[PDB]
Image 1 (cartoon, rainbow, N blue to C red):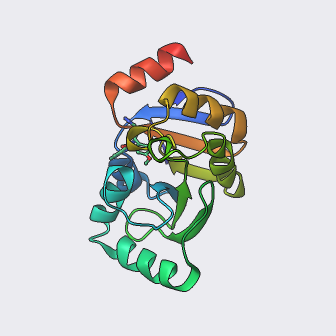
Image 2: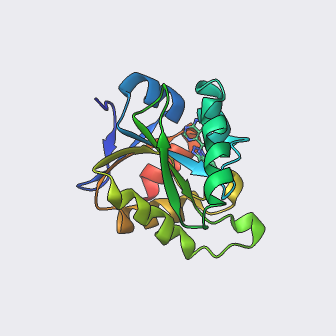
Amino acid sequence: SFSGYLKLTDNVYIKNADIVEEAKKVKPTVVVNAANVYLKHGGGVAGALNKATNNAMQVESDDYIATNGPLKVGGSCVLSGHNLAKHCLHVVGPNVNKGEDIQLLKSAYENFNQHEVLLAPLLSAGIFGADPIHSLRVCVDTVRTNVYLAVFDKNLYDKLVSSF
Ligand SMILES: COc1ccc([C@@H](Cc2nnn[nH]2)NC(=O)c2ncnc3[nH]ccc23)cc1
């Protein structure tokens, strides 16, 4: 049910939208979370997704961490999407602000290829320190499944589209 997306490639689409409001409107099979290895959903996409689930995402995440330990940088896990989606694919992109290797961003995007269609943010951008133009390039060059990108900042959306 995605609408108002601009087509970038055969499988990559983009919209200036809040991923939480997109998830509520569409109820996608998969919503991607921009997670950290601990699944501590404090801010950004994670804090926003968590708050929309009334903290049910954090409770579920803490139980997952208690059982399995932390995720790898570039890794992922599939948990419930609660009221936003059937599933939430928690993906850990490298945090450039913590000295994490930017090459792990390709590995993080590879997790998207296990799902036919996903609603997602740009990985490693925002508070994770990577260049969003670089993140979009890696997305297009790595993801083969149908990905619908929600870009929150209008000025960033315009820059991403005009430079692609
Ligand atoms: C920690 O990794 C991050 C990854 C991406 C991000 C940024 C990248 C970005 N910056 N301007 N639009 N996009 N995205 C969001 O914060 C974002 N995107 C879509 N819908 C949203 N609703 C609430 C937040 C939000 C930050 C952090």
